[PDB]
Length: 210
Image (cartoon, rainbow, N blue to C red; front, side):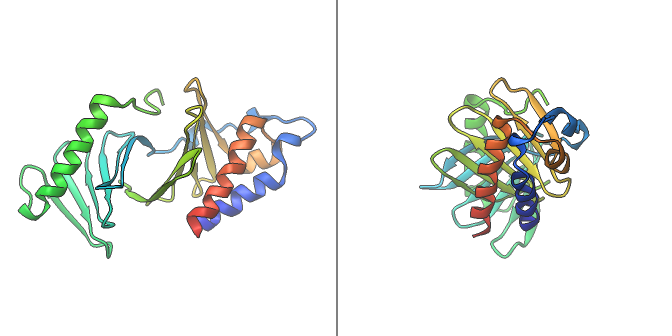
């Protein structure tokens, strides 16, 4: 799916969407292609523990430095644990093996920290975190359902990309959002703000693939 997203982005960017005779970005709108999941909060504590995050449904997860994952569902009790070989186990906070006490405790500190301190992205609008990285300008987040999310640090703008729907959602600096079909962006173009971000997205997807 990541390879497909790369080809999709490429086809849009090669068409030079901001250089079209009359760019008609509005023709590519498709509000029904809104993603089901995105990362609404995150904390990178990868020097010690890993990357904690909240999804837009209020679930929380941690990708630990040992490459295991623990996810707490929006119900506040259901847990899913994913080992390094991908093996999944299903337990509850209210009755869980003693062996996960430390990881559940850490997830709890992340959960409390995000709740007390951080703002919910897309609050006006189950996969797990497969990988992520940070550049100087952005954090790149790749979810297990193939979604790729890129949050820009300098202006709080974000892209959520889905190669299965071949769509992109853009959250601008006023937190307005709009979802576009990539094939329609290829046809009708888009303004410089989006075009620029999609060129960067392509470069990040290349990085995810390396």
